[PDB]
Length: 165
Image (cartoon, rainbow, N blue to C red; front, side, top):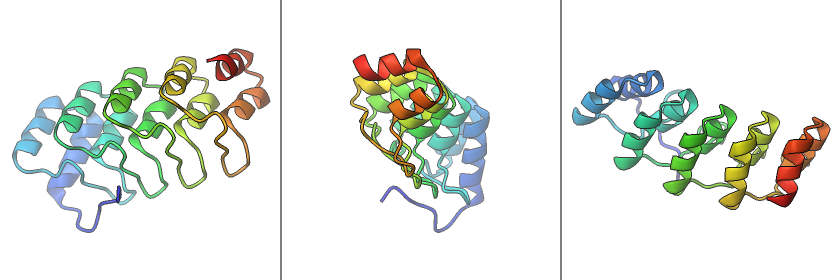
């Protein structure tokens, strides 16, 4: 599946750290020495998770170009698209979608990327997720949709986007 782990070499740990820190040269060097592009830490995060979380667009692109799993799940069920939407990185959201990210993947608690972007009020990311087929009816473990979250937070601008776009 989209879960890896099982070994955990320090070469893979170096790639995870370099990807999260946005070191383009070191990521290039480590991959040339055979670093697994899909390595995981104790939480199940891959280098693509950490580059998307920390907002490093150029690292995200070189990882995807070398066979990084765009839909990898960590132990909480979070995909790189979840993290890009949660941390508000619009261009990374777009690149992930362009590489086949599952727009409607849900984590352990049932949150989709649309849920996270709505909770944090990232209006443009919500619009982009909707254009790529985000499910407005998807409910989390509390039975709440992305639209319900915008109504409970009184974000009428976000609620209007979730209804008409």
